[PDB]
Image 1 (spheres, helix red, strand yellow):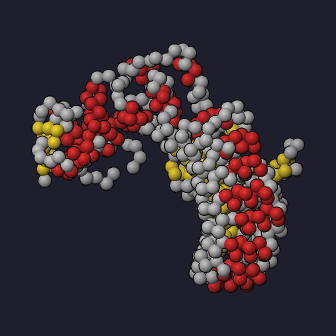
Image 2: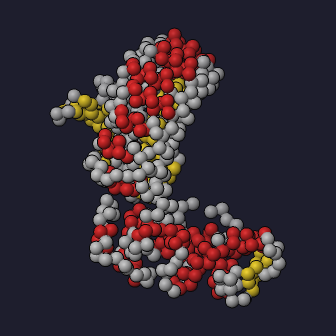
Image 3: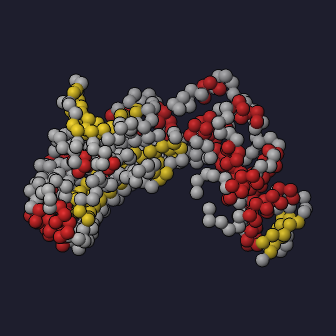
Length: 143
Length: 325
Length: 69
């Protein structure tokens, strides 16, 4: 009925056995080496809280194509900093649902935006010359 | 805080939500970003139907690991300038496209893993049909309307595809009785769907005999436009214990009355007999054979990638992720 | 009901279009082209050899045909 997870900084949380079961990482760990609590060194308390809140809202759901349910919609309305870890945590805890909604939100931040606007708003470099910059744009010409 | 340094896998995960145009866009953000944008997990299924592009591009795209390539009614009629390595494609449809026989040869020379292919309405060649024979795993092959190949190349192709389930070798105007005789003499006995219609005078009752003798598993047999086929052959159809859908449309010398026999085939579920039912009697035939469905399938579905119930953008049940709107 | 156009040509193909009553035109395949067996099944009646070679998306009821001279 219940299990305890220990975040990276130490903080301990208590959740339903199956709600945590949504993390393939936590399920893999639970089958062997067992006795609280489950240590998740790669997720701090702040992030783990959000993750547990998320996992709790779903638990059980009947839901198609890429949409980003009405709820998760605003749940991710968090600033860019937290979303970066929130999407990293999903990979770490292996929660299919989360990785999905967080990757789309990041995708939606690329839709209709030029490569320039991408470099900035996403803080990425640009090791492209003008030699390839434009040479690459010639290979994607057929579009 | 910064989004770079983000693990590769997770990036692809983000990239996999982008539409072909976007994906190509993020391709020019940072070399790596460009390296991942052309991964392989992202190019599993591609759909460029109706696109007009250069064979080199389509060649380069298939080399990114494409598995299901939907590209019918497209324009690729320039010469191949590049050279490629074996492709991964297992599902492809280039039907009713405008492709130079050489370019077609070029692309097909790199294929050996095709499971479902459709070159419907395309001019082929012996070389082409011969390298096709490399795809000995084909389950569904559509060559309806194709031309330009000897009965020799056809034989070798059929002797290779021994796991053929659906074969649509119809309306190959180029054919002679040589081809038809090769067809029935070399189709795999594992075949369950065969659409050999359109050969009117080159298909004899005998060939029907051969076929039946060699493919006890036919479930779909379409012999539309086979004039030489008159009721005296119906006995053959009884030899097919799994026959479910038969089509004899326009087999003129069939006495309406005689079609009544077919009703006796224990497994027959539908029958197409367009053009041989005098006007004002079809309803009689229908009523006489209440257990059958008569003249309800204007079109064939044998080895057709997309029978589509209006807007089915899938090829053989595969929905492509990459498409241009 | 079914309108058949005049045949014109280049130095290689013979061409013609067929207007379809917008009731049997609703049967015209959107996802593929029709073989001679299929268009005849539709009710189109013209010489043998004509091939339905391409789709005119703006007017699905106009079937474009062609054949070797």
